[PDB]
Length: 21
Image (cartoon, rainbow, N blue to C red; front, side):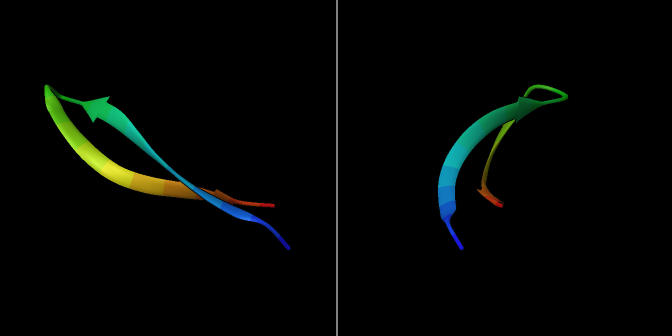
């Protein structure tokens, strides 16, 4: 498994998320 954290904008707000595949 592999998980990477990334940032993204939503409704004008930056949040901290990730992707696990």
